[PDB]
Image 1: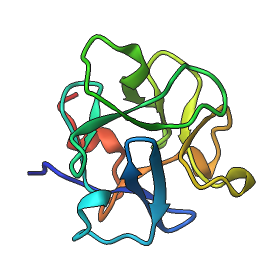
Image 2: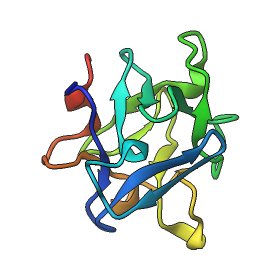
Image 3: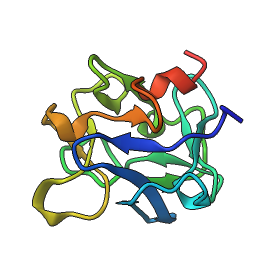
Length: 134
């Protein structure tokens, strides 16, 4: 299911890894690991294949942790969009899907737009929306 894919960060050479509803970190990329598989389930939501829960945040705030929530098409806290140059973040805000700062293991929302806020579909040079419907 192209439709499933791994979320990859070129600089760290690591992929997003869902550990639990309250924990989404990163790991060495393994396309056979269910916990690393994700898929768009709408124009703005990405669901973890392993947990059948959608990536989201408690609030649109800097350093908010990105974990998993029951998919809800009405919640703006789990809507994502592709910015420029593979920059990825919360829809309608300047907060990005980020990893690498402060030895923090969990994916975080960050105001910075450097190499750690940019993500591609593993195995390609395309942004995450290339596997979406939008």
